Image (tube, helix red, strand yellow):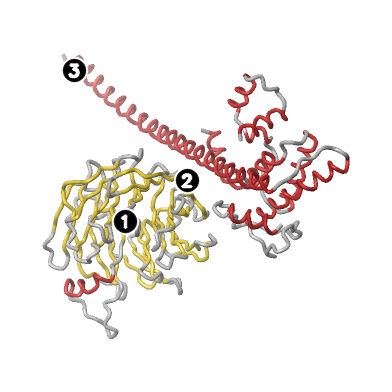
Amino acid sequence: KEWIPRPPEKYALSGHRSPVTRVIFHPVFSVMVSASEDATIKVWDYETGDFERTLKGHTDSVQDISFDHSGKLLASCSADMTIKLWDFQGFECIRTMHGHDHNVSSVAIMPNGDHIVSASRDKTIKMWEVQTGYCVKTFTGHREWVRMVRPNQDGTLIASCSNDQTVRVWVVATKECKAELREHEHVVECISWAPESSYSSISEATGSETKKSGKPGPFLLSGSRDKTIKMWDVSTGMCLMTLVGHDNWVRGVLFHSGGKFILSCADDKTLRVWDYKNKRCMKTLNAHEHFVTSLDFHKTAPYVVTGSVDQTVKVWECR
Amino acid sequence: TEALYQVGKEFTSKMDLEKPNYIVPDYMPVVYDKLPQPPSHREAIVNSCVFVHQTLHQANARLAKRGGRTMAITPRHYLDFINHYANLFHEKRSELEEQQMHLNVGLRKIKETVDQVEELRRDLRIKSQELEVKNAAANDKLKKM
Amino acid sequence: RERWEKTSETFKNQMSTIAGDCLLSAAFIAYAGYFDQQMRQNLFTTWSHHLQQANIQFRTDIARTEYLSNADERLRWQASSLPADDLCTENAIMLKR
């Protein structure tokens, strides 16, 4: 919906002793999960801002966490070179896949719910099986530290951004970089794709012409440390339009559930929501006293969450 | 034997017990007859548990033959065995994870310390240079006067 | 720093043997309570040999009494006039766990 965050906060959750790296929402429950730099993943009830529990399995700082479609498993990565899988019914680690040398930065479960992607400093992206834990295929082609990775809506296409200024889209079956993008002024840090409900809204936002099949094609977005947020086409690989105005380094980007606005956080201590179809909304909202690290938008509830380096997680209503 | 194996599987399903690089021995001491022929790490562990439980029966038989006094081995003993296994696994794993976390933090602190020591050295160099320039200036101004 | 680096290096190997070590310790706590030291040792040796034949990693260097109890607990037990014997230590561990 026209859900827009507002300057007043609801709860400023401060339980972490170390800077928070990422925050996500449970798919079904009224639960939000925050990973921080102290190797602990905390679980909160965002509706009332009540600390629920903590999972302290990880050795080094936890970097990225992700749920599945059903919300029954929680994939987590850390600097301890390992990927942990958490059973969310009882909240204990059930499978700790190793390998994938050096700090692991991002982890994600593609919607089929049977495999996991992982990216790390070792300049490659590994594929793991949830049931077994065997790395079955390894994606190479990034020449530098791969930062953030996200799959598609049906478990076939993957995007990997890295320090190497290139965003590469990979295919599950063929294991080939179908689209490689090298156009950013400085390092790309965060990526996120477009849901269904937004593709139509892109057509009049950019003027792109439909192909013979008529589908606009899958889409990307990439925010880069050069204070630029660029939204991209999977089928072609060409720029549609660019978002500029972020004061400092961008860290997190995602689309509004309605597929109409753009919500992004950056190291500019502020959260910016911007329109792209007609460039009307340019709302900047100070969020944290220090660097803001990550954010998330609830699929249905009018809530958003932001985790920052100040060891504090904040909740904003949407109006 | 099947009941013991099934109880072990169901009780240790929560447990990690996953070694990807597990090497199947050429002659595995098969205890549970229906064990899969290429067993996994978890299946081997449960087989070991069942073997332990039967080893207790053999020990009681050996004591009875010699004429010693034996206590009955009951399935409650097996339940205690698997419960202790679960608790010890969780406790030891968590303790190791905590210790490694704290040691990593300490190593990071020491590395930051030595880096700051290298910064202090160059700060001292700059201080020495400026002291030199100042003293030289003052000496030769006195020389002027 | 040197000692912590060594321990951090051997962390992965220590984590590799937790399953076997905990299996042996749990079996000892659950079963070996009634028997004398000779039969306890025979049972432990049988379990260790079976684990070896199954390619299951376990630490054969550490003593079970050290593995299942810390030094502070042992000192407290000695302060409770517990005999300074391996079998008595095992009995105290079983009375604890």
Seen at 68% across and 43% down, the residue is: C27
Check the residue under mark 3 and report the chain it is in. B
Instruction: Assign the C terminus of chain A to one quadrant of the image.
Output: bottom left
- Say whether residue A38 is left or right of residue B127: right
Q: Report, in whole angstroms, how far the alpha carbon at label 3 lies from the one at label 2.
A: 69 Å
**Residue A159, above or below B79:** below
> SS at mark 2?
loop
Callouts 3 and 2 close, C-beta under 8 Å: no
Check the residue under mark 1 and report the chain it is in. A
- Callout 3, which amino acid? Lys
**Which dot marks residue B141?**
3
Please give the residue where the numbered disc 2 appears in the rendered image.
A57
Please give the residue where the numbered disc 1 appears in the rendered image.
A189
Quadrant location of residue C96? top right
Instruction: Assign the N terminus of chain A to one quadrant of the image.
Output: bottom left
- Callout 1, which amino acid? Glu
Q: Report, in whole angstroms, how far the alpha carbon at label 3 lies from the one at label 1.
A: 58 Å
Both marks 3 and 1 on one chain: no
Query: Which is closer to the viewer, label 1 or label 2?
Result: 2
